[PDB]
Length: 185
Image (cartoon, rainbow, N blue to C red; front, top):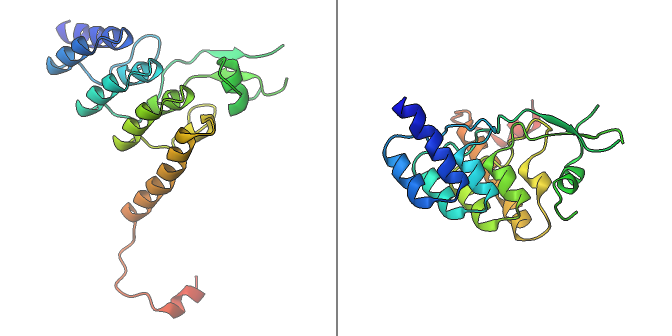
């Protein structure tokens, strides 16, 4: 049970913003990707907490930035279809009746950091390999949740660089590409 207990204690420490306990538990082999019964990982709850310090520690310990929230309850937001990103923000109480269903399933730490408009945590997650194009169950990217401002500007830049990196990784080997070939499929 020791291993299961370290996982559960790691999640409690992250939810409580206890950076010292998070670090201890990670060094003792707690599963950095463990999920709470409420659905979230330590990385996600650190993002909800706007704790960019704990986020950095988790990433340095190998946390997978692109795991999705397991919480699968669905809510009706009014008196179907997934609510829009703008109405999802409103439903969360943040600044700014057909599609009235809401779900957290699949939200990444980056979704939460952007919802919180937390530039420092957003930058940490992107620098640690978070995929800004990955969608949650409702089909929303983190950029869909951004307020205008520095987080939005950062995400636009990061989307372009992530797509560039992906295109370079998938690149096909070709020894020659004469200009005439641009005219042919």
